[PDB]
Each structure stands twice: as structure tokens, then as C-alpha cells.
Length: 263
Ligand SMILES: COCCNCc1ccc(Nc2ncc3cc(-c4ccncc4)ccc3n2)cc1
Image (cartoon, rainbow, N blue to C red; front, side):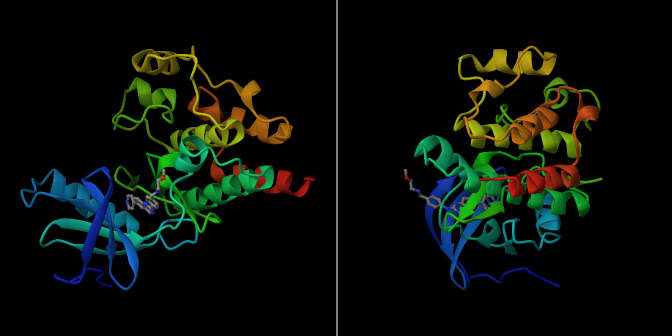
């Protein structure tokens, strides 16, 4: 298959954010789309190789809970195109507008997010930048997992980084478990309506402490009706040492099981 999208086809619109390799806009191409895109046609083989790699990953993802890849432009500017999510990111809902989701919808947002990752990890893909920001909500109902900028087979966003990633020896601290840890921090975002470590106000300290294992999210901050199995599961994903964290299959199952025992 060739998903290259010929020149002239796209009508690019309003700015949205600065994604890993460039700038996102709303655009049009057989309907509303998103277009992540590098503004310069000065594209060094560092930029032009990242792009080639993101596309290579996006083109292996066909799942309800992964953001639908649709195609790529080379000319005029480098561009990647995806489905447009009516509803914005999970970050926006939880922290910007403070949407008070029902506890069942929370558990489902978790369920679904886990499903996407599980699918991703079976396809042998490490997302490497999971976070509410990159989790998008479709008609406020369905979860779509986003920015594949960093992502691979075989960045000033710290709060979702496992300690070994904050630490650094290997060029390869990333694993399915380092993804599990970021997922851990999403469960917390969802169960607390809050980013972790708000008592601390100094970012560099957060970095140092997490990596050492002095800081770790305050689970007492969960909502009352948060099930104690969900409370116990956050703990599994947030376990300081990578080897004690469960992979997504067992996480799904646990969220599934706990969804069943539910008022
Ligand atoms: C305070 O109120 C603000 C109003 N919200 C505006 C709004 C609404 C919806 C979106 N939706 C949307 N929907 C999907 C999006 C996908 C990517 C994205 C990022 C990286 N790679 C591919 C796509 C990036 C941004 C995306 N944004 C954005 C802003």
C-alpha cells in the first residue's frame, strides 16, 4: 500500500499545538483531519528520518483505540494526517476544564487506553510518550491514543516517565513496562482528577526524586468510590523497579474483572 497523499489535496487550518516533529493544525481531506507537520522544507536527515519512522509505526496501527493514521505528505512541508477527535485530549478534560467524569466512565477510559496499548505492545511497539495530553476523546465517548513522535519497535514531559527512564543507562531504558508506568500515571490522573506531585513546585526536584525513588504518587488522593482493586493496580504500574510492573494483558484483565464487580 502507498498512503502518500499527493500535493494540493489538503486545506490546512487553525494551529493546535507543537507536536514532536513540528506543529499540529486542524485541516480538511475527505472530512476533518489533524495534520502534524514540520514548517521548514529545510529538513535534515535527523528530522527526515524521524518522520520516516513515525509513519512506519502509524501504518501498523489499525485499532479502535489508536488514533487513525490516514496518510503523509512530503511536499510542500512534511506532514502526517489522522482522524480528528471531537472532544479534545483527556488532559484538557481532567485538568483544564475539570470535567467530573462518572466513576464508570473513568474505569472505561482506563479499560480502553489499556486496550490500545495492549494492541500496540502485541504489534511490538513502545509508545514512549503516553500521557493524558496524547490520549484523545472521541465524541467524549471513545479513546484514541495519539502522538507517536517518539515510538519504536524492538521531550520535557516528565510526570509520566518511569524512574529508569529519568535515570539513563542503555539508550534502551524504554520497555513495555516504562509504558506501563506512564499508564500508571494516567490511572492516577483519572482517579485523582490531578497531576502527580502538586505539593512540590520545582520541576527539577521532581525529576531527581522520582529517578531516585524518593517521590511517588499519593494514592490516598484517589476518589472515595475508586475501587481498591484499581487502587491496588495503580501501585503495580507505578512500582519503582521495572521488573515488578505487569504487562498490559494482565492489566486489561484486572480492569475488566473490576469493571464487573461494580455498582
Ligand atoms: C478551553 O477550550 C478549548 C477548546 N478546545 C479546542 C480543541 C478541540 C478539539 C481538538 N481536537 C484534536 N483532535 C485530535 C488531535 C490529534 C493530534 C495529533 C498529535 C500528534 N499526532 C497526530 C495527531 C493533535 C491534536 C488533536 N486535537 C483540539 C482543540
